[PDB]
Image (cartoon, rainbow over all chains, first blue to last red):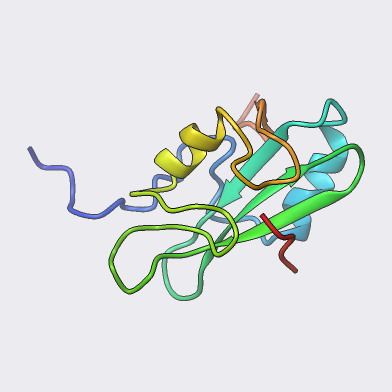
Length: 112
Length: 5
């Protein structure tokens, strides 16, 4: 297989930037969104926790995302998922609790 | 800073 065990912080992705802070992405959201549904998850790899960041109608939000000493990621008010891929994709469906469902990746792109 | 899901 050769593909590491746990998610090796799959930076590669828009709505998944394990670099941004929280504001940095919220200013980015400032750029894109409006349509209520834009979002971008953040998850580094060193120490701390992840957090979903989306925008409603002009009020960026953030949702702490962590597991439960079980190994699976989740959210207090949100839900419970395996990884940010499920909590994201899932939520890509609905809000599940967010202010509003998801619709688009917010964070920036790459190069050009 | 975490809205309530």
